[PDB]
Amino acid sequence: MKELIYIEEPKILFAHGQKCTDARDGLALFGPLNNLYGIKSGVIGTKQGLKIFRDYLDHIQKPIYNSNSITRPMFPGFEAVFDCKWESTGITFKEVTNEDIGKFLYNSSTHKRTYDLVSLFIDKIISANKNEDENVDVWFVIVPDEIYKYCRPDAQFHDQFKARLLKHTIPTQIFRESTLAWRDFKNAFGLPIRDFSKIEGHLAWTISTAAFYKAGGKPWKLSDVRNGVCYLGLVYKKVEKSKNPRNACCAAQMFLDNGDGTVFKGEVGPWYNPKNGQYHLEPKEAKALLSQSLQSYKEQIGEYPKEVFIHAKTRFNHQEWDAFLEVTPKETNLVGVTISKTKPLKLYKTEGDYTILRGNAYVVNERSAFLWTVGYVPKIQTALSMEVPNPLFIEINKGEADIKQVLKDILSLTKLNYNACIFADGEPVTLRFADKIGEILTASTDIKTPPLAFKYYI
Amino acid sequence: RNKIFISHATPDDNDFTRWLALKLIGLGYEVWCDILFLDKGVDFWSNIEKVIREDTCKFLLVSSSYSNQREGVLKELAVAAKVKKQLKDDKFIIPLAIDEQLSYDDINIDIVRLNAIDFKMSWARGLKDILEAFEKQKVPKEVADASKSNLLYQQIFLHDKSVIEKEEIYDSNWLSILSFPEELRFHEYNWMLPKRFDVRELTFPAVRYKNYLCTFAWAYDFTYHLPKTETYHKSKTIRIPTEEILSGSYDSNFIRNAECKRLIVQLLNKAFELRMKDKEVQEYEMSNKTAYWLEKGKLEKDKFEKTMLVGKQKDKNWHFAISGASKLYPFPVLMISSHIFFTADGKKLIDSSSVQHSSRRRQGKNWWNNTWRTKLLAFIKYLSDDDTSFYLEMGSEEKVFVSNEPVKFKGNVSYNIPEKNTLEEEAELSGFN
């Protein structure tokens, strides 16, 4: 019998040392771990965007309800959860006229259109941070829902705009009007395009916990963690514009228990392998990245990591690891983990209609296992993933570590998505924002940035 | 007397009651209300009245459009007024104006003259005002403690939503393999293999490893496009027991174990691809592997084994389908991947792939665990040749028996299956993340 193992929910620490699994239950019931007191806004957008933001803030002040409050709980109200004042009285709103966006939006190809319009929305923010003495915690970019519509997917406006801000380190949050005033935008019929009516309160949750996080917020933190667990996430992105098919860019997201990760942009070089399409690092840049992360960890913590798990979506060759094992203190345990997504092992259930649980895992051997990060969770009484859950294959490619420990860490790393206040997620945070960070890095290639937190990436 | 009693129109005001009670318990204000007491007795009203008369020190009143209409709210209000008159207190009763629609006139005549703490603009401001009053009226409160609120919340809202130590049996998509051909043969064809001849197009699988030809088929198994092989000598051929290869005991410098296992994987994949040609199952080209489905009308009402393996969604027809891969570690199996293929009429295929993916997601939304399991098992049993397995053709005498019943997995902890509320709510929803 191919027995499975259950690994309990990681549990997340909240304010006053309160440990609750759901992100938006111990948040409302207690509040954020760090109690920052002012989220003075700097909304940038059209006047209509300012009105939408003001109305949505007024809504957020009053409770918003979900039709299914068993699965998606409500929002008691910002100040009733975050005990801090985020209202429409204090706003450093900076206006962009409709014609201003229009003239920068009609430039034929998406290339010039996106570059010019991102520069338009970036010059205003840079000037605001430079020549004004009212330092607002977060800059809200309320983009009218025509840039996202007309200027659809470098592509991904959301990513290029965030990427060309790392040097200035301006914590910014980007919103769409259709996300805020979803009722106002409607199709040919009277039904709005985005029917959030059953999840309206949910839209109030994620929009809040993200904005709080970017305003120097720490909504929550892992409860059970070891003393030095530095998690490296090796993102990767082939430079399609590069004439050399080998050329590629990489980074390394360093994570402590705090859930706020530092991005160590790597060096663009020959990391692609078209013969088998596998990301690989040569000794020089491998040592450079590992040394950068190690020095940053020592500086922030005062000592070198006790353990270092490098998670990746592929397998590390021998040059990579033989380079990594050189620039690493003897008193350190370095491990390399491969986390594949599909690896077909669907497990349907004979009993009934609902799907398999979330903690179930199949351990193939001492160095391989399957983990069900998605599916049905009793607390929500719902399936995180529709259809049947797809497992997650985890193998300890290099180094010696306990597979159960790696599985538990990988499950715990799924509760650190501040950007979206949800029960959990299907991927660990180390590789969760792999495509996003890869596109950010590709957008910002020539400029070299130091170690920066996620507040400027996600 | 310390309880901060609350009355509300349940279930019209359960959320506000729970929120306010938890906040007041965390901040120290001990609270009492209908919720938080799921162990209701035969006579709950008696205990409520006893608490109001004796234990309650403040009487908050959730004032909503349906709070005044409800009879229980009015009864609790009358008892509160009686106790207040007995005590001769100015503000033993506090209406919490939580509803905008409740007009000034509509307010129940027993609370119109009592100043109401506002909640319409913000719940936080209302709680600030309540705390200010409680400080003014010197309402007792213990030291702030947010652990008790956590424990109470877990015991109340998270008692029937916790995993249970129950065993469940799951059906995988890994279909076992019973028997392999006795030996794997590497033929010394050398010059007998035509130059630039694609061995992929052959009656039986064969991999041109090095200068040899690796396969389970006999030397003479192929003669149509290989007539010269009639003169081949079996002495030169190399025979390696398949059992030894799979067990891993085999060790030779000519070829390593891993390469042999990869060769066997490719042979199994090609064998399945060839075998599905005989069956009356269509073909769809996936990214790398191949996918097989059933066209319209081949089965009697598209209900093989009383299971709907083909149906109609709006203007198109959806057919359930599979795709086969091979694995050998930790035990030989055929990986089956469910698919839904959408066709204009039931015999052709949709050229576009974006429409295919969109319709696949849309149809998967409407299907769930039971549907996917039933359709996969039905399709696999359809491909069966007998009541035990189906065979892939490697050689004239050699065949590989792949079972038609997937491997059974077992958990240790499980949950309880409530009604299909998720099906009732999630239906007709897309793009909300």
Image (tube, grey):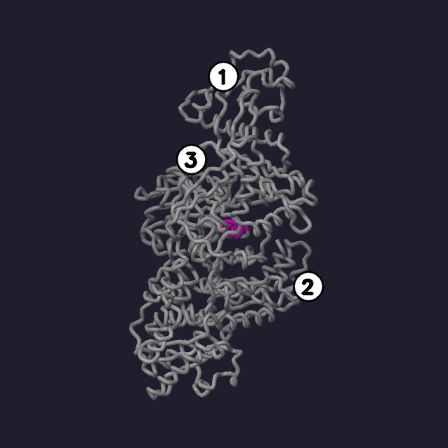
Q: Which residue is mark 1?
A: B238
Front: mark 2 or 3: 2
Task: Estimate the spatial distance between the alpha carbons at disc 2 and disc 3, rounded to whole Å.
Answer: 59 Å
Q: Position of residue B337 (x, y in %)?
A: 54, 40
SS at circle 1: strand
Task: Estimate the spatial distance between the alpha carbons at disc 3 and disc 1, rounded to whole Å.
Answer: 34 Å
Q: Is residue A58 above or below residue A67?
A: below
Q: Is residue B351 visible?
A: no
Which quarter shows the N terminus of chain B?
A: bottom left
Which is more N-terminal, label 3 or label 2?
2
Q: Is residue A405 left or right of residue A249?
A: left
Q: Is residue B324 left or right of residue B46?
A: right
The amino acid on which the numbered mark 1 sits, given as a three-letter code, is Ile
Q: Is residue B419 above or below residue A267?
A: below
The amino acid on which the numbered mark 3 sits, given as a three-letter code, is His
The amino acid on which the numbered mark 2 sits, given as a three-letter code, is Ala
Q: Which residue is mark 3?
A: A318
Q: Position of residue A454 (x, y in %)?
A: 46, 56
Q: Quadrant of residue B377?
A: top right
Instruction: Say which residue appears at 40% left-offset and 43% top-offset.
Output: A4
SS at circle 2: loop
Do marks 1 and 2 share a subunit?
Answer: no
Look at the image and give the residue range highlighted in magenta. A433-442
Q: Position of residue A333 (x, y in %)?
A: 33, 43
Q: Which residue is mark 2?
A: A188
Front one among B326 and B12: B12
